[PDB]
Length: 229
Length: 216
Image: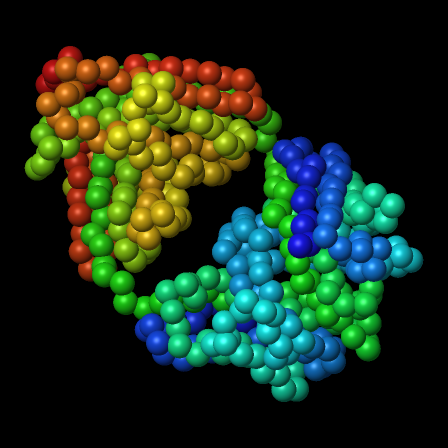
């Protein structure tokens, strides 16, 4: 079975470089043309490059020509993507793919991508790494119809994704809901993580959200407590 | 030049025939064969149709392809729940020497019970007020379909600016979630009696209300 595994992706600032690699197995690598295809968050598939079986020629998308180089090492069954002078519009998931035909594409013939890899994410942003500011979202004294009290944490203005939030050191998993983060106009992210608890407990028990932002190494525990009312 | 054109969406009820078109030029579809891919966003696509009308083994018989001139289509003959994904067509352009994707189509399997949203509203934290900032958070869960309209109101009046709202995102639930954040100054916050988050979903509007009344 043909496997393609992409590697190298990261978070960089504009003008900087990366190199992606795509390691393969389950086929005679040197026989096929190989692709790079990307996908910008919320957008469609966009072809980046192709390289012939023997690497004798390579073709690029207009947007990338001159900043990107596709190359291959048929000895080590690996495909590279050298990405220079990276631009925020290059943010995406990068896939390698195999061309299913006879080593190239032409006016005669082009099979197209047959097997794909899993993707490696690339983020190019003007932002720098920022740890979050962590605020408790205290459980309201205002009753609600039902056996509900909601409390949470606000994980505000971080970069980059992701962040890890657990509750009571992950000893609480029941009725936690951590929402998808917003990407503010800042370039920074914010998320919220809520626990709906039976209002009887609120005050009988203690709730702390544990927030871990690996990229910054910002680890914060916020105790979330009923207001003095 | 750069793009195949697809309709942004195609829908139907389960068991119907749903087809997807893909409009190109002389230089790509007119010249070369067309592939179709099925993809869940950000995840690896999968080849569904190659060389206009061929199918790889494992692909269901209800998928067919067709091409003529500079146009191609995908047919789904008996729409099933599994078929809710993105679809791309693709082809090599002999003039540009490039491999061109279609702009892509989302399918939705029509019906599915409408689900009202759960609205949960938090006022600014004390500790964030000390930092001289204020965020109000409106969290909106367990809705279907994924189309909501969030408004912010202060006393009797629509809140101008400072609103960030996420685009709704499907849960494993098959229902949606969305957040909305209102940024103010602690003085704005404190200069009103009440703040509301109002969410309108399929002609129904839910409102939650918070007040600077911590122990007042």
